[PDB]
Image (cartoon, rainbow, N blue to C red; front, side, top):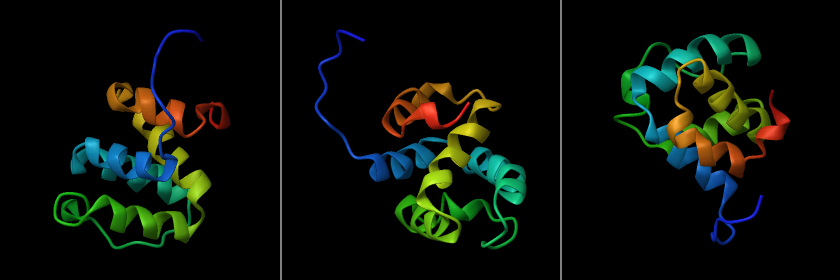
Length: 102
Protein backbone atom coordinates (compact mmCIF):
# COMPACT_ATOMS: atom_id res chain seq x y z
CA UNK A 1 0.00 0.00 0.00
CA UNK A 2 1.18 3.49 -0.91
CA UNK A 3 4.52 4.26 -2.54
CA UNK A 4 5.95 2.21 -5.40
CA UNK A 5 5.60 3.86 -8.81
CA UNK A 6 5.40 0.99 -11.30
CA UNK A 7 2.96 0.69 -14.20
CA UNK A 8 0.98 -2.46 -14.96
CA UNK A 9 2.97 -5.57 -15.87
CA UNK A 10 2.36 -8.95 -17.51
CA UNK A 11 1.43 -11.94 -15.31
CA UNK A 12 2.20 -14.67 -17.85
CA UNK A 13 5.58 -13.11 -18.65
CA UNK A 14 6.18 -12.95 -14.90
CA UNK A 15 6.19 -16.75 -14.61
CA UNK A 16 8.62 -17.14 -17.50
CA UNK A 17 11.01 -14.51 -16.15
CA UNK A 18 10.60 -15.79 -12.59
CA UNK A 19 10.94 -19.53 -13.23
CA UNK A 20 14.06 -18.59 -15.19
CA UNK A 21 15.34 -16.30 -12.44
CA UNK A 22 16.11 -19.46 -10.47
CA UNK A 23 18.65 -22.22 -11.10
CA UNK A 24 17.49 -25.36 -12.90
CA UNK A 25 18.54 -27.33 -9.82
CA UNK A 26 15.93 -25.30 -7.94
CA UNK A 27 12.82 -25.10 -10.12
CA UNK A 28 13.20 -28.81 -10.90
CA UNK A 29 13.46 -29.75 -7.23
CA UNK A 30 10.09 -28.14 -6.54
CA UNK A 31 8.36 -29.29 -9.74
CA UNK A 32 9.76 -32.74 -8.98
CA UNK A 33 7.84 -33.07 -5.72
CA UNK A 34 5.33 -30.22 -5.84
CA UNK A 35 4.27 -30.95 -9.42
CA UNK A 36 4.48 -34.70 -8.78
CA UNK A 37 1.63 -34.41 -6.27
CA UNK A 38 -0.05 -31.07 -6.99
CA UNK A 39 -0.03 -32.00 -10.68
CA UNK A 40 -0.34 -35.29 -12.57
CA UNK A 41 2.86 -35.70 -14.59
CA UNK A 42 2.98 -34.25 -18.09
CA UNK A 43 6.71 -33.75 -18.58
CA UNK A 44 9.98 -35.65 -19.16
CA UNK A 45 12.16 -37.22 -16.44
CA UNK A 46 15.11 -35.62 -14.64
CA UNK A 47 16.49 -32.94 -16.96
CA UNK A 48 18.47 -29.91 -15.80
CA UNK A 49 18.47 -28.70 -19.39
CA UNK A 50 14.73 -28.12 -19.23
CA UNK A 51 15.50 -24.67 -17.82
CA UNK A 52 19.14 -24.09 -18.75
CA UNK A 53 19.07 -25.61 -22.22
CA UNK A 54 15.45 -24.91 -23.15
CA UNK A 55 13.51 -21.71 -22.50
CA UNK A 56 10.92 -20.63 -19.89
CA UNK A 57 8.35 -19.53 -22.47
CA UNK A 58 8.53 -23.08 -23.83
CA UNK A 59 8.53 -25.12 -20.62
CA UNK A 60 6.07 -22.73 -18.98
CA UNK A 61 3.60 -22.73 -21.87
CA UNK A 62 3.56 -26.53 -21.66
CA UNK A 63 3.10 -26.57 -17.88
CA UNK A 64 0.20 -24.12 -17.94
CA UNK A 65 -1.44 -26.26 -20.62
CA UNK A 66 -0.74 -29.46 -18.69
CA UNK A 67 -3.09 -28.75 -15.78
CA UNK A 68 -3.69 -25.01 -15.99
CA UNK A 69 -1.99 -21.62 -16.15
CA UNK A 70 -3.50 -20.85 -12.75
CA UNK A 71 -2.10 -23.51 -10.42
CA UNK A 72 0.90 -23.52 -12.75
CA UNK A 73 2.34 -20.23 -11.51
CA UNK A 74 1.32 -21.13 -7.96
CA UNK A 75 3.23 -24.41 -8.24
CA UNK A 76 6.34 -22.32 -8.85
CA UNK A 77 6.03 -19.93 -5.90
CA UNK A 78 4.46 -22.44 -3.51
CA UNK A 79 7.42 -24.74 -4.07
CA UNK A 80 9.88 -21.86 -4.30
CA UNK A 81 8.99 -20.71 -0.79
CA UNK A 82 10.50 -23.75 0.91
CA UNK A 83 13.51 -22.93 -1.26
CA UNK A 84 13.87 -19.38 0.07
CA UNK A 85 13.53 -17.89 -3.41
CA UNK A 86 11.52 -14.97 -2.03
CA UNK A 87 14.15 -12.81 -3.73
CA UNK A 88 12.63 -12.61 -7.22
CA UNK A 89 9.38 -14.23 -6.07
CA UNK A 90 8.73 -11.01 -4.17
CA UNK A 91 7.28 -9.42 -7.32
CA UNK A 92 6.22 -12.50 -9.28
CA UNK A 93 3.94 -13.36 -6.36
CA UNK A 94 2.58 -9.82 -6.06
CA UNK A 95 2.07 -10.02 -9.83
CA UNK A 96 0.34 -13.40 -9.96
CA UNK A 97 -1.97 -12.75 -7.00
CA UNK A 98 -0.19 -14.47 -4.11
CA UNK A 99 -3.49 -14.22 -2.24
CA UNK A 100 -4.48 -17.29 -4.26
CA UNK A 101 -1.86 -19.32 -2.40
CA UNK A 102 -1.21 -19.59 1.34
